[PDB]
Image (spheres, grey):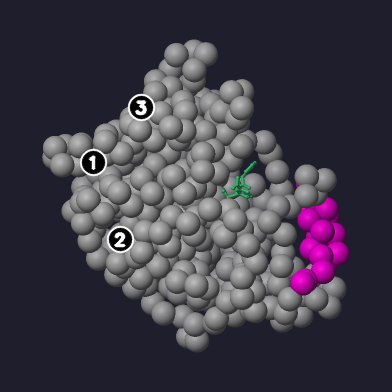
Amino acid sequence: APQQINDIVHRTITPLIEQQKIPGMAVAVIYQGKPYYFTWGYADIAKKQPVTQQTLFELGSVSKTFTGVLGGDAIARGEIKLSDPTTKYWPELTAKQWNGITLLHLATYTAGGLPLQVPDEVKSSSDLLRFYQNWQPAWAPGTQRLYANSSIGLFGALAVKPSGLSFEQAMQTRVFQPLKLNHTWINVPPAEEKNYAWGYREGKAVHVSPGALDAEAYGVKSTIEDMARWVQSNLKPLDINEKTLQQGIQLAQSRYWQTGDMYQGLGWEMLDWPVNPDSIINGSDNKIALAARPVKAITPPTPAVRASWVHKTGATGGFGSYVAFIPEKELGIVMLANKNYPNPARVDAAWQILNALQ
Ligand SMILES: *[B]([O])([O])[C]([N]C(=O)[C]C1=[C][C]=[C]S1)C1=[C]C(C([O])=O)=[C][C]=[C]1
């Protein structure tokens, strides 16, 4: 790889791993459209397995970017509309608070305070129905943003209903396969287990546990190579041959709501480029990222802006991931690690690297 990329990447990531005590990590930098890979440490400490370009990491919430794009693809296919009422898909949601809550609200965390996490006791489809029927909104629809798995997770489940496919099958057929993400999974097959890194929480090896709407909200696992391809696809959706997918990616980067200097897309989050590093760095901290904030509707939504810093943080109990890219510069980065370390450190490192290369 060009020495400039090698140097900034190593000079930034090496101290990060030491400071955060990250067991293993993989990084891909997309520069002028080409990917460059880097790896460090262990995927499995006990078994001495190193992290390689084929190592699978839990993406955690970066999965929401796939859900957003799959949802966009469904819109493009004319299967659903963001303006559709939630009840059009789940007529069983008869509780009055659902009146006026649309797929857009679910996808963008603006339904009125749907909770960050789906309760552990909620497992089955009837459990899920009961949970949403009982939920009491804190605010009217479209007034406040509260990042939530229960919100975009429900969006994902409903978005794939007309297709007649399960969420996994729709994702495989409509997103993974067309983009050649042949080592990206919602469920890791036994044959691939040898490449599945262990996550580390308080020193113990862990993998994500089954949960309601896990697939839709935080259940994708992937390699640094497939994630680099994911960044390339979102950087240049026009290079994609499948029409509805190309459109779907575009729709997920449209700006639907604004809060502070951040715009909410479908899964992805965006800021105008150039960005103020302190804004995205401090903004990534959960103290802000998970906070309830009033939002301004962007009427109508702004189509994907090429001069944007598009990104998403993701975590599971044992993993910490981050993806960020700037369409206008054909520049991007993916950072996958098997430790859930502070978001601010992830974004600061990504900024140092991309700022140096821009
Ligand atoms: B997402 O924002 O990364 C989301 N992830 C998950 O819910 C998956 C997890 C399963 C067990 C622990 S996280 C999320 C992340 C966090 C966080 O900052 O750790 C909190 C709530 C949701």
- Count of marks, rendered view: 3
- Compare marks 1 and 2 and give the one earlier in the sequence: 1
Name the residue tied to disc 2: 326
Secondary structure beneath label 3: strand
| Residues shaded magenta | 123-138
In the rendered image, the vertical position of residue 219 relative to residue 283, given as above or below: above
Q: Which mark is residue 40?
A: 3
Give the labeled residue for mark 1: 8
Assign the magenta stretch its main secondary structure.
helix
Callout 1 environment at 10 Å: few (<14), some (14 to 19), or many (20+)?
A: some
- In front: 335, or 107? 335
Question: Which circle, 1 or 3, is nearer the viewer?
Answer: 1
Q: Secondary structure at mark 1?
A: helix
Query: Residue 245 lies in magenta, yes or no?
Result: no
Q: What's the residue at 31%, 39% (across, down)? A: 12
Q: Quadrant of the N terminus?
A: top left
Q: Quadrant of residue 6?
A: top left
User: Quick one: 178 or 41, which is closer to the camera?
Assistant: 41
Local SS, label 2: strand
Q: Position of residue 132 (x, y in %)?
A: 79, 63
Residue 204 percent coordinates (x, y): 61, 23
Residue displayed at 55% across by 81% down: 296
283 or 89, nearer to the observer: 283
Task: Name which residue type carries label 3.
Answer: Trp
Relative image position of residue 177 (x, y in whole percent): 41, 48
Q: Is mark 2 within 8 Å of ligand 1?
A: no
